Length: 67
Image (cartoon, rainbow, N blue to C red; front, side, top):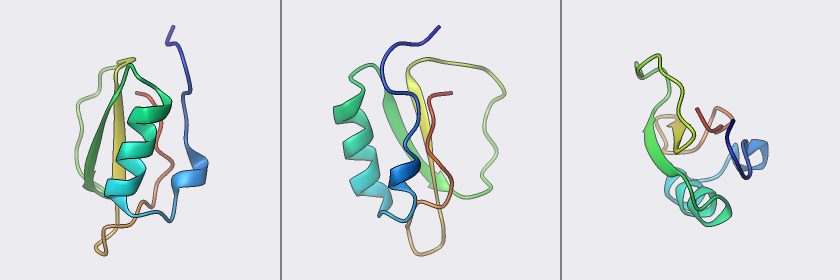
C-alpha cells in the first residue's frame, strides 16, 4: 500500500516538465518520468514511480498516477 498523494488529474493539460516537478514536490517518495503518450512500460506495480504521458507538444494527456 502506497503512502501520500496517488493521482494528479489536475495536471492533465500542463507541460510535462512542470507536472513532473509538482508531482515530486507533492509526494516525496516518487520519481516522475515524462514519456510520450502510448510508450510501452513494464507491467509491475511500484509506490515510487509516476509515469507522465505527454502528447507531441509535450503536454500531459493522461492522468499521472503512482504505479
